[PDB]
Length: 75
Length: 219
Image 1 (cartoon, rainbow over the protein chains, first blue to last red):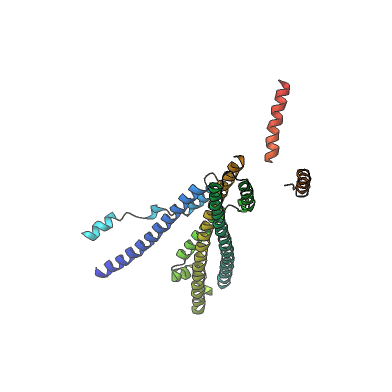
Image 2 (cartoon, rainbow over the protein chains, first blue to last red):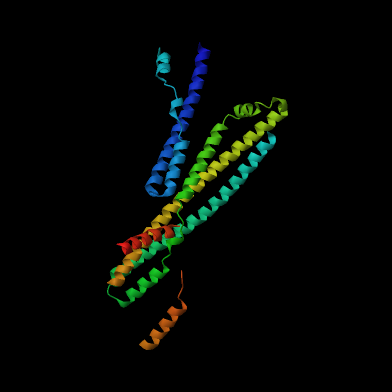
């Protein structure tokens, strides 16, 4: 059980590191998009930039809910 | 596999070299723009001081004309929004590639799938070395792209500030301007004549105007 818990904790740490990197990238992209919208409002390239940002935005639907895992770990 | 990896590495190196050259050019342009903005700010301060001190003087008009002539033209400064967007997209793509290549062993195993008949220990070692080299090149390219994007943002901000300062100075000069002789006149006319210079959508605009004119003629 301890070995399984250690493996699960390592996997959770890797997932948390990936999620933190994704969140930092998303925050940077949001700041860049806000700056671009404030600076180049009314420009044709603004639509292309927004489309590229939306395409590059990650999908959170692949992130499963961690409430059940947290409850099981607490128990 | 090895040839494809080598070609990808060569393309990445060429892209990194091009990005470095573009970043150097952008840094030079940003330095020039910063120098121009500092000169414009100094000239604006001097013009304001001269207007406040020597108001109503004949030499004030000549000083304002000289300042306007020496003022740089911002029309030669192209918009950097598209370049900034392209740099941001390239940086995002490089970051995504680096993240996908973070697990070098997993990437090598995935690439070796479907080619086990041409995979050996030496082949795997060469693939791992090529993956490491590609990851290093991608990291260097991402750093260069970030530096170039920062330089482009700084240059765009400096250009916007310089354009605003130039517009304010032009408005101030126009407001100030608003607020023997025979020989000089022929000489001025000759100088003006010698220094004289000449600088789809239009068809569509003309067509509606022609239709309006035809309708008016009919009515």
